[PDB]
Length: 94
Length: 190
Ligand SMILES: [Cu+2]
Image (tube, rainbow over all chains, first blue to last red; front, side, top):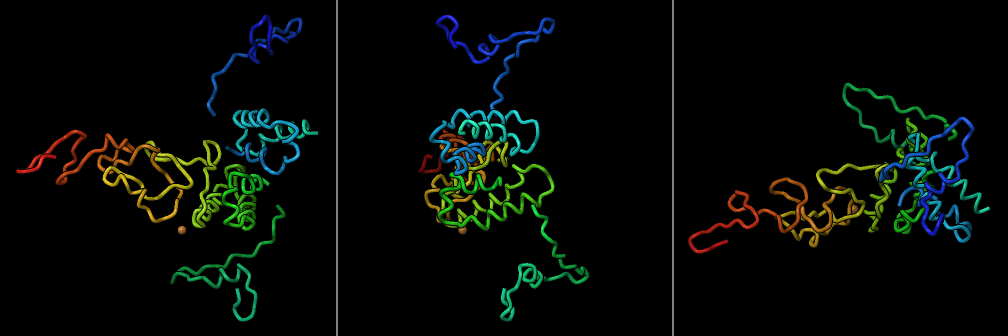
């Protein structure tokens, strides 16, 4: 996150790693305002399902990711947007 | 469930408690075989209801939540279990517990008039402009509903939602006054 003694935002860091195709000049993503969108993610991750995994891998980053995945859901059922983050947390615990 | 030394099923008991209308003959529900169908496990066993587990057992309500999730006709599975959770919160309040808020903008949202907020355990004796000490003299346990934000009281005079105490109006002889307004009699000045 440091280019020359400065601080790089995650979007800038991601844009710095682009390698475009010879003819496909893909446009960089445009930043969006925060949608402002204890919950189901907190109950699931802080519950007894992940008891030996919390002491090894911190939950806060994955909890925040779960909240973002829920907020950017494409379907109505909220139980289907938490599968990806929970699976990733289980992978990291393994 | 014991008619005469006989273990009645819930279906039989419910049918026994029937009282029909004169011209409306009703058919008893047909006992259907199970459909062979765990979201509720996370919230009910989670810390969100922890302060309620010690008072009301959750197994019956866990089964009720499973039945509600399986039996409801839309795939709003996250938002199709609000009724069982609300009932469990009600039972926790009736058991002397203090449930904490479990709802949200996307998870079982509740709409409150004016600037009030929905809460799971607050005193039902709402403080108004006329009675600003009602909550401190309440005998009933905490209930769930729409309540004024902390630091304000309900406006029962102008019906303009929750207002601060310093801006509450006054009533004298059926006429609503304003903060700072005065009236006088022969030998008083209020
Ligand atoms: Cu009660």
